[PDB]
Every structure is written in structure tokens, then in C-alpha cells.
Length: 44
Length: 49
Image 1 (cartoon, rainbow over the protein chains, first blue to last red):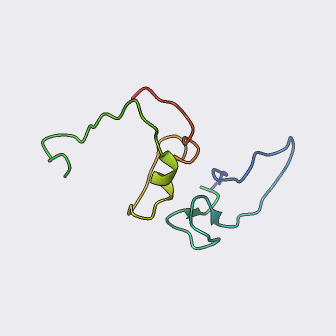
Image 2: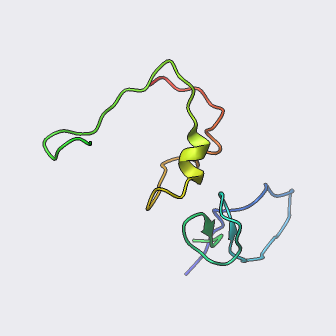
């Protein structure tokens, strides 16, 4: 029901509310979207 | 060659440089999982064994 951000590019500033949910590159793979291998959806 | 089902693959690695980043980044694995943080973040860290 409730989702939490696990994968984020950088840490938040105090009282920042950043709610973009775009799937993006974590590792070596040059992609956005294309979830799998080394690109992931940010929340669980 | 890997440990049979009657043995666990337990191969001590010591006194060396650990390229944790390539293990994560490489496409040769079918899947990768880690308990803590990705090997690219562990890439410049020191461990016991």
C-alpha cells in the first residue's frame, strides 16, 4: 500500500519532498526505463 | 569448477586488490544481489577476508 524510496541518486535536503518515480541507471548500463540488470525502479 | 552439492564454495581471498566494481558492472553474470550496498560503492573499501 505504502511505498518507500530505496534507490535515489543523492541524499535529500532537509524538508525536501522529491516525488519523481522515473526508472533509472544504477550501474554500467546506459538506460532509463528498461528496468532490469542495472536500471531500477526507485521505490518498493 | 565449483563446489559440489556436498561442499560450499568458500574460497578465501586475502592480501589483494578487490575489483568489486567490475563484478557489479560486468554483464557476464545472469544476476547479482548484495546484502548491503552495491560493489561499486564497496569498490574502495577494506575487509577482513
